[PDB]
Length: 189
Image: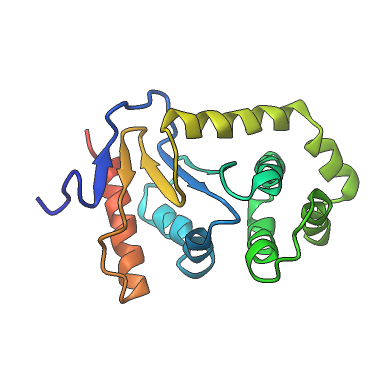
């Protein structure tokens, strides 16, 4: 087969009912995740290959970066609640990995302020129970798939992407293979 269970993807031994159709996990501390988002633009290219209106979900994880890592999971919940992911993803990645200026929860807040989210609005969302619920959803989704590494992509709660053996000598060819593979997995019956 051109797509083989155990090679380009794995079938979860314990599938997850009700899971998002396309579910990515990342950490702003995760170096491959910086490449995936800032250089390869994996999420955007998967989106362009799936039908218009499929739900893609992207969650942050707690198991990298200790205290600040868990602060970033709560900040990502704020980003999802306010719908400002496209404004803060680059400065959060660069603040953690490029300039390394994000060292406290206040430094995270500064990134939102600089991106145009008013301090009053960020603070209200940060302390809101809507955000607490999104934090819980992120933790539960990770536990549902027994998540131990990032970046990770899961399709229909049933399949995990395995990019590790794919040819990465050409970054556009690799991104296309990745997206075509997600599309194939989404179409499995």
